[PDB]
Amino acid sequence: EDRRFQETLDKIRKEEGYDFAAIAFYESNKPSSPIKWHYVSGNKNNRFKLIILRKGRGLAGTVMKTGKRMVIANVGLALGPEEKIDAPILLSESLTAVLAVPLWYKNQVYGVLLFGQRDGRPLPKIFDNDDIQRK
Image (cartoon, rainbow, N blue to C red; front, side):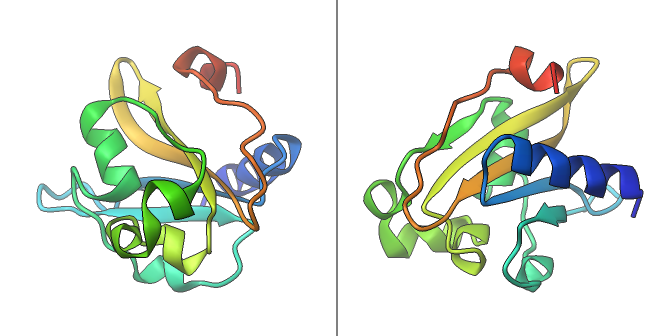
């Protein structure tokens, strides 16, 4: 699905030092549309395709709603096992740290770019909106 998104995601994930990256967007242009993880890079499995999110729910839904990045430097401490179910990509990809940033176009949030670490690897660097526009 537009190979440019996939290839760019793969390049950026690796250049930024991440074990995983994902982009979430609305599933369709219908008013009831949920949000889905449309593109992933460094994924262990394809279960991300089973995830259905709503505005305000999970990492992607919360960022879309608030327009604010979410940073979790250590998942095991910050959330523990029970809260992970609210942000199911953390379960399917065993993410131990995450940086989720809004994707803006003309002052609207259209998507969420998620960077994830596994195995306790720390986040290398936290990006701003300005930084992500310098993508």
